[PDB]
Image (cartoon, coloured by chain):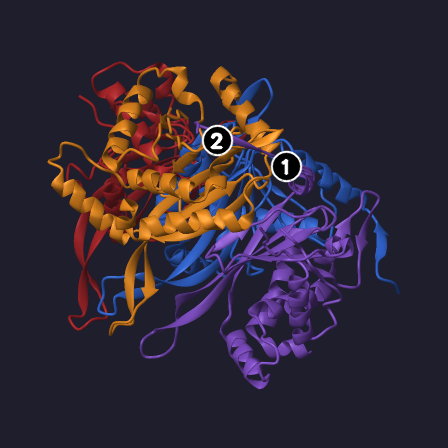
Chain colours: A red, B blue, C orange, D purple
Amino acid sequence: AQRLMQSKQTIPHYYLSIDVNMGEVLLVRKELNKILEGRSKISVNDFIIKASALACLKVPEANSSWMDTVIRQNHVVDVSVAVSTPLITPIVFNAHIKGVETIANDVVSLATKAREGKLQPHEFQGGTFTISNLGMFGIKNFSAIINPPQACILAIGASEDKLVPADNEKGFDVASMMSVTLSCDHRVVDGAVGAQWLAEFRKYLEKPITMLL
Amino acid sequence: TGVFTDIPISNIRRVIAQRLMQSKQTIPHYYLSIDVNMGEVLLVRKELNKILEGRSKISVNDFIIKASALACLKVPEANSSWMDTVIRQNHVVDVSVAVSTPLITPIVFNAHIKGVETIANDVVSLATKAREGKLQPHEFQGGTFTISNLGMFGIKNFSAIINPPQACILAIGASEDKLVPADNEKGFDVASMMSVTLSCDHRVVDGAVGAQWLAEFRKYLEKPITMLL
Amino acid sequence: TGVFTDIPISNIRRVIAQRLMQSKQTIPHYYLSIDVNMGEVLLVRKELNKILEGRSKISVNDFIIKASALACLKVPEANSSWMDTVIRQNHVVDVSVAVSTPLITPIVFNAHIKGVETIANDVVSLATKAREGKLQPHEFQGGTFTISNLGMFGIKNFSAIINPPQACILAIGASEDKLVPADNEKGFDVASMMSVTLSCDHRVVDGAVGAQWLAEFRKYLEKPITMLL
Amino acid sequence: TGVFTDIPISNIRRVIAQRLMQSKQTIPHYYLSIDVNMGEVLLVRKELNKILEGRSKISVNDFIIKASALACLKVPEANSSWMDTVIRQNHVVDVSVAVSTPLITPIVFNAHIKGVETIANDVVSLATKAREGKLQPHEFQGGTFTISNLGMFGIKNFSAIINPPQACILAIGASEDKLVPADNEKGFDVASMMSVTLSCDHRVVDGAVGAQWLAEFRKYLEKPITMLL
């Protein structure tokens, strides 16, 4: 409550939003799960991690922190996942490098160490980013408040089935849509770059092979 | 003229010649080979080149780098070095590319991490610094691996000798069009095939693991999306 | 951790490493190769397995043993050893099988005589005594021949180095499905192909006889009933 | 008898054995390979044999000689010798043919000049002087090149070791019938294929030129009239 009252009383928040067409990621996720023996499941959440990290590389200022003297800009990406708990927050370390499946295994081993057992304090340190998704609960859209060392949050909505315009005989087709919102510090993230960040994230997810680049 | 003519032996040629004579007189070499069906990589390469503005070309050679590096992770003992007291096994992958030159050898550093396009740009900037200009000695150090491909010259298959700090080489043949069996009405279809050979130290690489290495490399290339894992 | 890590060199690994370094530094190796059409052996193997109650499985590897042994009889000089004073030519065929192990090498004794199923049972009882238990030293003696196959691992082709008392190795590739020309309406048919390579000493095996050896081996396998002769 | 038997090592066999042990213990060997589509040469060979009265047969081996010689001209460094002080590069091409014998090696002198039929007659008159009669020592001198083919014996592919004054060998496989892709209604056609391997010294032959050599050889044989140029 002190973290929240403090940060919403200091950081000048603002909210940017988009829609992300998740079909292609659904195909690749189905396939990599087929290729894995069942040795390890892979969630959509892992692609979410991988992409948001690479985007933090492409547009660094969404991945920095506001210290009072100087703005601190960090070249390694930690990403903390906001997991609900009867609000434990494991950090995935150096996610900008490690592959999607090691990210998935990392987030599960961290969840097992969290949901029913104690974690070391070292994992709660709120390092450099936060994803926070509530699509399981059926929330369509939501805007979070952020934790003060950092400058941004990523809030993910429920995936849904909308009728987009098409070129076939029917004139339309179904599409999976995720509404994605992004809060920013706005002393460090001016709106055009928050938008640039959301742009790259949108492209790494609309076109998943470009994660290889 | 006459029946024969002589020219003095070059200095750098004697350096290389010492490396080669030494290593083929010490390391117990042996040769494993496979065929790799390159069609899917050709599709993904065409597409990522389409998505790039032409801001940067991407060769097949870069996928070759990325995969051989990740395989070095999956099967570490093909990526190690034989020191006389202990076998030295290194958790970071450097990969040196054997580029022909009127044999300059740039190293791509930490290729196990960096993405395919930064690997492509790295190998070109290293080639520009090599083919017509001097490189720092620091780049010739033969760190931890070597790819060496001669498919441009139309060689189908070839087995190289390796440089002694390391334990292996990857030699890549020309891509070609073979008639594999199929299930359609015709009963067959065309396929792109690359013959890939791999030399090993064989005090450190026993045959089953050299094979395991070749297996993973084959799967990262037959099924390119698994490079994401 | 760090950029590299070290582990002490194993004792048995140094024994093998001495065998390998020694033999690839002494024996003048060379590599002959063929393709062997394995369909007929596949039919006979299916049938003899059907006729056996399941009392004993039979692998393709056993036919490989039986044939290579009979060929050693037909062309003796591929089955001999180079001693410094005289070439030693031995009228009994032992055959050692190079089995991968986390490289244990059981010998099948007098395989030139015993039938295919006793050869299969011999190689399994020897594998059971090897993979998880100690063997007597007497079985590691490298007697007079070596088969070494890596088709299970998907290797297509490979050339091994040999162990110095002997003069040759047989390396077996993966079986595969190639489209050979035919005489029917389609003009072609599928065929099972095994690529088989054979290393030789080449002070004792001149190329025409290494080839003769490979010839007989090819005929005992292309036409399996002639194993009865 | 007994389990083994011995025969004294032959003198000439020790001479050859010294040549082989020496050269595979000194020269840093490596192996390049291609496939050569032999159909057109088969047509021209059939025709020139038809035009000759039967006054002289012509083998495929003669085209092999003519082409490898002209290629030695186009890419000189595959046709030179490694002396310790300087690399010796010779503007005349001798070519020695490795003929099997119960390993006699006649040399065809100045083959870069003489026509295909005089090359054929030269190799037969040299074979007649060799297989059942003594040759002068002057013909065994291993001058500047060696072809060595084992397609008669059905070997598909093989890599030889070379004799130390020289820097390379050409090993020729059996000609075979593969199903290449085509443009007609069937989608494919039969092709005659020869697998050709080439060993090199690799202090004098860097890989791109060994490849260049193999390239020209491939073109003189794929397109036989260009032998006239």
Of B103 and B73, nearer the camera is: B103
Q: Label 2 belongs to which residue?
A: B205
Q: CA distance from mark 2 to mark 1?
A: 16 Å
Q: Secondary structure at mark 2?
A: loop
The image position of residue D97, as x and y in percent, is 65, 59
Disc 1 residue type (three-letter): Lys
Disc 2 residue type (three-letter): Val
Of D225 and B216, nearer the camera is: D225
**With A17 as the anchor, is C72 left or right in this view?**
right
Q: Which mark is residue B24?
A: 1
Instruction: Say if labels 2 and 1 share a chain.
Output: yes
Query: Quick one: label 1, few (<14), some, or many (20+) residues within 10 Å?
Result: many
Residue B37 found in image quarter: bottom left
Residue placed at 41% from the left, 66% from the top? D177
Residue C24 visible: yes
Of D135 and C23, nearer the camera is: D135
The mark nearer the N terminus, 2 or 1, is 1
The image position of residue C43, as x and y in percent, is 21, 50
**With B118 as the anchor, is A141 left or right in this view?**
left
Residue placed at 45% from the left, 44% from the top? C75
Residue A110 found in image quarter: top left
Residue C204 found in image quarter: top right
